[PDB]
Amino acid sequence: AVFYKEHKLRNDGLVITTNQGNIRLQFKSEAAIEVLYRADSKQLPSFALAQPESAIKAQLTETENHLQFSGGTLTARIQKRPFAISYYRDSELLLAEESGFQVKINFRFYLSPGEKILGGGQRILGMDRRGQRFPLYNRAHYGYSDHSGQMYFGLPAIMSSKQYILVFDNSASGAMDIGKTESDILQLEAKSGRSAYILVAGNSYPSLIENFTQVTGRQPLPPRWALGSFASRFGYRSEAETRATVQKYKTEDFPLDTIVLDLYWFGKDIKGHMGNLDWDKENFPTPLDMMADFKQQGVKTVLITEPFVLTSSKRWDDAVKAKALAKDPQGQPKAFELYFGNGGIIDVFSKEGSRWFSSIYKDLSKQGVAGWWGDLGEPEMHPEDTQHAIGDADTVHNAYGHRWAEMLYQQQLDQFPELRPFIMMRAGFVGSQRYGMIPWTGDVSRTWGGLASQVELALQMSLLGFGYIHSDLGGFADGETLDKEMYIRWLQYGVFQPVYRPHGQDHIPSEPVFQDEETKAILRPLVKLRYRMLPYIYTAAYQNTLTGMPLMRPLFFSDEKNPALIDNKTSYFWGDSLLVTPITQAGVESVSIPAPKGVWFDFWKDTRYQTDGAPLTLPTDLHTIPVLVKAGAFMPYVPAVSTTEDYRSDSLEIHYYADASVPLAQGEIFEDDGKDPNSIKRNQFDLLTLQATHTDNQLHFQLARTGKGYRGMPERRATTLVIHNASDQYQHLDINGKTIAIAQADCASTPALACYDQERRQLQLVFTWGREALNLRLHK
Ligand SMILES: *[C@H]1[C@H](O)[C@@H](O)[C@H](O)[C@@H](CO)[C@@H]1NS(=O)(=O)O
Ligand SMILES: O=C([O-])C(=O)[O-]
């Protein structure tokens, strides 16, 4: 029983008083509002908000039974009696409180009939999580396959088919009930922590995500090397074995940017060494030489680190002395029994813990470490009586990984202000992307079911801020012998998802270079393709940094007025132009692809398909997975390199998928030095744009470059433009007004500047793309 009492304004912030206390409403933007209940009282701070203390001028109108607090896009309508806030985009009702807040923390809201609800982060439950209830408590799900209610990286957030996102801005042990218990109620609970939610609206799923990342944080562009090939296993046992793996990528002619060292780098056993955070010199005798030798070959070294310091580790006494570990209520170091032994947890919420841990990361980075892997940040074990500087384990649990990332990100920026941090972690919070967190889906089983779940997990995380969500390619957990077909399908899919990191327990090889001749003959040209496609992938990365647009986009983006598409977790967009359908079972001979209506091409075979809605049936082979290209796509390639350290776009090859159904099309290629964290902010980039105009008698391309450029940027790029499905009726090409005849023979066999291959329906134009605008005009 709750009712309006009064309200004031304070720094664009509405402070409402009910019978039961204060509520602070602040627009963080024109489409996003923070609703803090118990505003009078001391709470944990926001974790989700990039700018917690921000609030923008909103307009306030008081009526008889209601208030209205509007930002521009988003309207909070505050019914006085009974007390209930609802939320409008213009006058479209998004979300209405039921009971709203009840004081354990509780929030209740109505669900509309037929409303579909994505969210919760990593679960394997179906894309629409409506009808589900699950905890908000980051926890391991070792060896998961085709089902999970609770894994490494939950998010206290949802995305509705009404096109809002709701965030429960609370770090504590909790639960989400999505109209499970009560068909028409969504309920958020926590045992403790901040009593705050955040509503974000958009006109579309893309502008919703732009709105969400605006207020929760934009991922800084990762180093281009994060888009390369990783050598990883659990785990390289020695310097010799690590050097032998880098050598195996060289002798097997697979691309390699980064080798990842698991927990044997700091001790000879799985158990009893964690917290050493220093080289096991018996097995890694010359690590500085090792990292420098790798850097000469363009290969980066990434080291695993964990929150736990064992009482058996060389750093126990020092960590206790420095007060770096979390404490019991008595005030001693909290020790508890992990798989690895008895130990404590570094308190990343404390000054002493942050400085102690930071200092260790600084020393190892100085020795030559390029990037960082933080495993077990759930935290994996976190007894309820553990005491952090700001709260107990159950209150801070879901933000530990978040703050660990922040700590490590700040540290890397202060040591190397001219480099982009690489921070790979298993657990974080809403907004962790702003600290460059790159998550993976943990200890997935080596099963088809484990593979079949990855698109669902990736889209669920991508939709709520995590563009670089990926899987251990090939699978991680148990098995006794390689499932070759599964492995191949997993590393094919890998090419078309964010981070190319095969990884698994080392009783079965995870790295493609250790596979049989057939497997290498299939995967080698696909790992090269990943590198040739860097201009496509790096451009999707750039768009992610700009707008939060995830690299993997769900099928439902193709038609926002067809909510039935929301259920799809078998087909997704890799950037704007590729519809990928991974094969997730053995012996599949053909697939039915629910391609949006329009024209589509087989990425592998150039075959043209049109559909008015009917799905497309494509046969399958072991060599590839089904990928369709959207008519109007510009697919840019550079020559394959072994390492992104050698990346050049002096030679470009661009494939344009022509069809009269697409009279207007645009592409862009974002180029910078691949390393400068300030490139976008300072416009130290080369942004190539291509526009196609396709009419009955003409096909016109406009090429341009913006940005201030960057050191080593090519002035002039040798460009091969390959036009797929080109009309056989074009006779003349103008290039900036200069007329060139189109050859109709021997295109593959002459240094032709314009040649039509009649057999392939491909028109090839070869030219110089310099800094000035270029127009190419084909006419019948
Ligand atoms: C953490 C992580 O999920 C996995 O990739 C890693 O190889 C191991 C060992 O460091 C960790 N999982 S654990 O074996 O369950 O500890
Ligand atoms: O697309 C065209 O213009 C054609 O097919 O000739």
Image (cartoon, grey):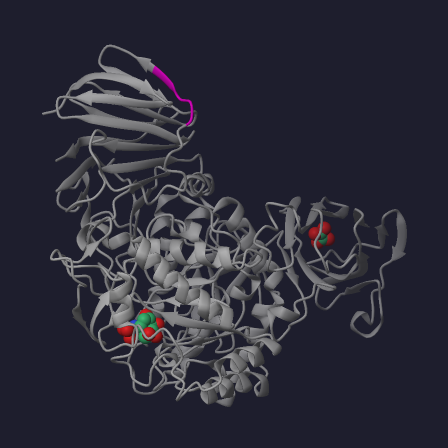
Q: What stretch is highlighted in magenta?
A: 56-60
Q: Residue 502: name its quadrant.
A: bottom left
- Going by the image, does 646 lie left or right of 185? right
The chief SS type of the magenta part is loop
- Going by the image, does 285 lie left or right of 194? right
Where residue 645 sits: x, y (%)?
A: 62, 69
Residue 346 in sight: yes
Q: Which of 394 and 414 is in front in this view?
A: 414
Q: In which quarter of the image is the N terminus?
A: top left
Q: Which residue is drawn at 27% across and 37% down?
A: 197
Q: Nearer the viewer, residue 314 or 569?
A: 314
Classify 523 as above or below 377: below
Q: Which residue is drawn at 12% across and 55% down?
A: 329
Give the residue furthest to the left. Answer: 1
Where residue 321 sits: x, y (%)?
A: 26, 65
Where residue 454 sits: x, y (%)?
A: 36, 64
Whether residue 612 is in magenta: the answer is no
Q: Residue 748: name its quadrant.
A: bottom right
Classify 225 as above or below 130: below
Q: Which of 157 and 566 is in front in this view?
A: 157
Q: Residue 18: name its quadrant.
A: top left
Residue 143 in sight: no
Give the residue furthest to the top. Answer: 64
Q: Which of 201 and 603 is in front in this view?
A: 201
Where residue 350 sits: x, y (%)?
A: 29, 53
